[PDB]
Image: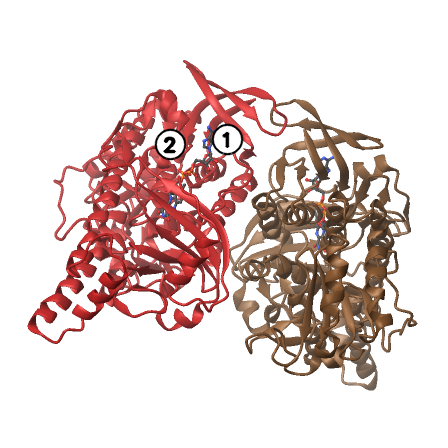
Chain colours: A red, B brown
């Protein structure tokens, strides 16, 4: 066997890598130990960035037609049981009109609810169609690196055979216990994730629309520990989660209690368990090996950043491998994979963990014990209806506590979108870092400075709305400018013919292909109309010029050659 | 390797077979020579029967959320070009209110538009998830049958290795040039399909909603030969088809002419060719080999019966192999596969071909030549606007001709649903064949007589509509009766414990789990309320009793033992 890139793993990171590589004409052989694509629903939250990437390749429309949309996952209800009395609700997943606006202004896509069970196979099938060899029931065993590529040993669970595959690079998208990471010797840190804890999940079917329809929500939390009624399909498919474990028909009981009532005909599906040693990789790259996904970041499910962050890891490295394999870019370009993705890995492991320190306070608000029994939790409901000044501080305390839990339920827009890149793959412009005017975890800050992702705004084509993001991507470099920067079209030519690289230029303005109809691009560019913003295949701005002056024009070439390593 | 059933092919028939077998707990290893699932859109029409089967397994909702629905494929427009003048339209795919009612009354599902490109992978991924081993890039080379199973030789296009797989049965779902059919020696007939002719298909993208939206249609025919603008995704994705061929950028020209105007920005995709030696197999079964799909029926694309008929071939044989492999049924049960599916194979090859003799008359109506040039076809448009009595006969002639083309565009409801089974797997009741009151190709006739598929009617559960079909299926035998046939619950028990077979009984009536709310079941059963209708896992009624009399009750056992071959 001989492939350009061996992809170990077919989950979110692997499938995406194979689809993008194929889309770029690079031969890749993605493997996966199991029969199917994952069985449980696992991850479910799809953030804007993941959507954008789905939109770039043409998989958004299908994605949206298998997901629950944003309007059905805004009611986060804290209660005793589903059929019980509530404590309160929070506007989850940017439901609050303010949060919704900030959401809508940051990108043309929007939160949706798509379980991994359906997302996986959509991407695996597309990778194959796009020309990426796929092969399940084949496990990676190890590899040996050498100066011209790698050879790896594969076990085939169908024939029982064993074989080698020669590849130029390997992508370690093999999960939480990456054998690829262990072989490459990648250092891991921040294991302080407390005491290694797991979760137990149970699937079951019931028709609980009568207790959902009027208050449509992605999840219904129960205080019972902090159990959780997560919707899989509205409102007939479910799952309970709570905090390596055996259970039986008794689970049906647990649920009947989690539903409060035992009258909706329930059908108990599979029962899994999930453990996690919270850690990141300090480095994601060793020689010709690159890891990504849970293979570089392992953490809690708070904020659902794991599947999203993993697809973004694949987006950042695909075009890069493709440019290097085609000889248009020097192998150095690959060094920025670690530079740009590694800080994202550590950032999310810590944030996902920090969010776990927001729930506990809801208990302390009900002046309760973590191991509340019944009377205790029934006496809390009483103390809460108290008509005294001390009942007010109390109710106020509980509202405060619950509202503090939003950062882990749709409130961390900054965390999802505020990616700042520093590396050879980004050509600095000379300006200083502007900062964040407001909290960088909670609110997103749009920025055209090199290192940041393009900012969304709407534009028009045939008088129909198109987003700045639609103009770019496509496995190519993008240059955006206006009418007065006409000179950018030629520069770009001279710098593309000479560098053997594709470089699409768009001159936005009146009577042009794309038009600044609402004047919003002029508003969000942070530069004259004659300036230019170079956009990488992954949507990040690496180069920014303030005008079309000879000294601004001459710099393009220096930036591209620099970004490519030549 | 060792599997219970080797499935050669992963298209519609193979994927479905693997999903159903898995669903029945039978170990199956489905293979496929290619990388992906098919690339072109190929088949696109999904008939009611295919839907029903999707609904039984739980894949209807997903299917419906990737398809164009019935309301967008009712306007069949005959024109010069898309942007030209029309000759006329026909109500395709049961759009006509009368046809729509007959459609809606025959089943709880409805025509939809889902290309094979999306349908394939939905079913392949589900088969894997359900526990069916899948493996592409593996080709079948041949096999040797022996009295206890078969051994087949496989070529692996990934490792280059060659290996054997031992299986009890093989399912030849390998297409139009089935190597499995040739090895099993299956006789083929009715090659008279005239002179072997092909079609050329071309994909392209344009935004032609401005010339579709007001007249939503599955296809736009152009008279140019009989070209055809088929929609893939409304209304940006397309394909032209017309009557082994090379073409280039010039195709873009062909289309610009097929669109009439050259102003919509067009993007030329792939260009394939499709050939077909019209033939059926006289027998579909040899020893331990069973063929299905195009491997048993090859024909034109008129009436889109091929993909539907192929899924139905898999539905008919899955439960059967499962009962035999579990030792609950004698190997003889498998003999009815040929008895019941074989006549369907010949019926559709001939019908698909006959439909090709309905188009030609539209020309003779315009008093034209098959090879019309331009002036000729422009002079036809003139002769058509003539204000004479001879212009009237003419316009009337053309309307007649076009309306005759409906049998191949949604008019053959009988053909899609009028399956009559005769075999050991059906226990006759003693009544004679009732016939069809109206044309058996055009209109469907519901019939509770053994050998026919359950008739759809609505019933209620929790006051919510459920279709008689929903009560049955599930890889099990189903007995339907009413309040006065209470005795059927016990009989069924005695006959299920003793035969080691699952047999669900439903007593439909007032205050029961299912209720004849609209009295429609009482109306369509053709028997007393005390009677019973036994339904096979494939939705076909094999046994029918007129009442709960001791002589009617005692017969159940004799029928089940007979249907199973014991
Ligand atoms: C049970 C469970 C429940 C979860 N629930 C949630 C949730 O509710 N919310 C949330 O945000 N996140 C959840 N996660 C985490 C989430 O699944 C990850 O963030 C996401 O799957 C990362 O994608 P990945 O492809 O990197 O991981 P994976 O998809 O696990 O990548 C590894 C894949 O490669 C294959 N593979 C592994 N080892 C080998 C080998 N040696 N050889 C060949 N192939 C191999 C495996 O088939 C595996 O599918 C859950 C994880 C698990 C396990
Ligand atoms: C180009 C094209 C266009 C078409 N367009 C239409 C249309 O517009 N309308 C319509 O109604 N019908 C159309 N058809 C016919 C339609 O595709 C068939 O009715 C349908 O595909 C039947 O399903 P199947 O799985 O039996 O066929 P297939 O899916 O072809 O079954 C064979 C499959 O098994 C695999 N296989 C084959 N040989 C081997 C081997 N030796 N070893 C291992 N694996 C093997 C192949 O990968 C192949 O996918 C078209 C067919 C083609 C080829």
Q: Secondary structure at mark 2?
A: helix
Q: Determine the chain carrying the residue at label 1.
A: A
Q: Residue B254 location, x and y as percent?
A: 65, 53
Task: Look at discs 2 and 1 and give the one toward the viewer.
Answer: 1
Q: Is residue B85 left or right of residue B300?
A: left
Q: In the image, B426: left or right of A406?
A: right
User: Disc 1 on helix, strand or loop?
Assistant: strand
Give the x, y percent position of residue A220.
Answer: 34, 61
Give how far across and how far down residue B366 sits, in percent: 80, 71
| On screen, residue A80 above or below A115 | below
Vertical relation: A100 (above or below) A182 = below
Which is nearer the eye, A130 or A17?
A17
Can you identify the residue that label 1 sits on?
Answer: A28
How far apart are labels 2 and 1 at the CA level? 14 Å
Say above or below: A334 vs A205.
above
Q: Residue at x 84, y 34 (%)?
A: B183
Which quadrant does the N terminus of chain B fall into? top right
Numbered mark located on residue A19 in the image? none
Give whichever of discs 2 and 1 has the lower sequence position.
Answer: 1
Within 10 Å of disc 1 (Cα), the crowding (few <14, some 14-19, many 20+) is many
Q: Residue at x 63, y 35 (%)?
A: B136
Q: Is residue A287 left or right of residue B253?
A: left
Q: Nearer the viewer, residue B500 or A162?
A: B500
State if disc 1 and disc 2 touch (CB < 8 Å): no
Q: Residue B275 or A365: which is nearer the viewer? A: A365
Residue linked to disc 2 = A320
Is there any visible trace of residue B373 in the rendered image? no
Residue A313, picture quadrant: top left
Residue sitting nearer the eye, A562 or A422: A422
Q: Residue furthest top?
A: A146
Same-subunit check for callouts 2 and 1: yes
Give residue B30's position: percent from left, percent from top.
67, 39
């Amino acid at each position: 066997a001989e492939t350009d890139v061996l992809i170990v793993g077919a989950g979110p990171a692997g499938a995406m890598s194979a689809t993008l590589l194929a889309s770029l004409g690079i031969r890749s052989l993605m493997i996966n130990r199991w029969r199917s694509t994952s069985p449980g629903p696992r991850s479910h939250i799809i953030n804007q960035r993941t959507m954008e990437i789905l939109r770039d390749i043409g998989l958004e429309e299908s994605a949206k037609s298998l997901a629950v949309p944003k309007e059905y996952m805004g009611e986060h209800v804290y209660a005793t049981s589903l059929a019980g009395e509530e404590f309160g609700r929070i506007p989850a997943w940017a439901s609050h009109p303010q949060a919704h606006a900030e959401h809508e202004l940051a990108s043309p896509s929007r939160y949706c609810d798509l379980p991994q069970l359906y997302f996986e196979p959509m991407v695996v099938s597309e990778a194959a169609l796009r020309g990426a060899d796929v092969r399940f029931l084949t496990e990676y065993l190890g590899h040996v690196e050498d100066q011209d590529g790698v050879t790896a040993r594969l076990l085939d669970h169908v024939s029982g055979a064993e074989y080698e595959v020669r590849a130029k690079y390997i992508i370690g998208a093999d999960g939480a216990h990456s054998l690829v990471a262990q072989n490459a010797g990648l250092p891991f840190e921040g294991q302080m994730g407390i005491g290694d804890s797991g979760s137990i999940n149970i699937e079951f079917s019931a028709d609980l629309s009568s207790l959902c329809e009027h208050r449509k929500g992605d999840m219904y939390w129960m205080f019972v520990g902090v159990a959780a009624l997560r919707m899989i399909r509205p409102w007939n498919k479910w799952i309970c989660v709570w905090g390596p474990e055996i259970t039986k028909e008794e689970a049906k009981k647990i649920i009947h209690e989690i539903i409060g009532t035992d009258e909706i005909p329930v059908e108990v599906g599979p029962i899994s368990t999930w453990t996690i040693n919270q850690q990141y990789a300090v480095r994601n790259t060793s020689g010709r090996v690159f890891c990504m996904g849970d293979a570089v970041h392992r953490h809690t499910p708070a904020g659902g950043l794991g599947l999203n962050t993993s697809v973004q890891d694949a987006y950042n490295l695909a075009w890069k491998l493709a440019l290097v394999l085609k000889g248009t870019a020097a192998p150095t370009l690959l060094d920025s994979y670690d530079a740009e993705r590694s800080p994202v890995a550590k950032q999310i492991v810590e944030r996902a963990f920090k969010s776990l320190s927001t729930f506990p306070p809801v208990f302390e608000a009900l002046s309760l014990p973590p191991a509340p029994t019944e009377s205790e939790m029934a006496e809390a409901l009483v103390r809460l209806k108290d008509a005294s000044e001390e009942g007010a501080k109390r109710r106020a305390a509980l509202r405060k506590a619950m509202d503090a839990t939003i950062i882990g339920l749709g409130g961390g827009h900054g965390v999802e979108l505020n990616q700042r890149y520093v590396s050879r793959a980004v050509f600095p412009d000379g300006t200083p870092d502007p900062g964040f005017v407001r909290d960088q975890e909670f609110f997103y800050q749009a920025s055209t400075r090199p290192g940041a992702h393009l900012p969304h705004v709407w534009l028009t084509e045939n008088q129909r709305r198109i987003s700045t993001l639609d103009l770019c991507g496509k496995g190519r470099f993008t240059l955006l400018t206006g009418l007065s920067g006409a000179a950018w079209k030629h520069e770009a030519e001279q710098v593309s013919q000479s560098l053997g690289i594709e470089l699409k230029v768009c001159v936005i303005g009146p009577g042009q292909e794309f038009v600044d109809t609402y004047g919003e691009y002029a508003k969000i560019s942070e530069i004259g109309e004659s300036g230019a913003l170079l956009v990488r295949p992954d949507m990040f701005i690496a180069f920014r010029a303030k005008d079309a002056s000879r000294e601004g024009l001459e710099q393009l070439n220096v930036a591209v050659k620099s970004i490519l390593g030549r």
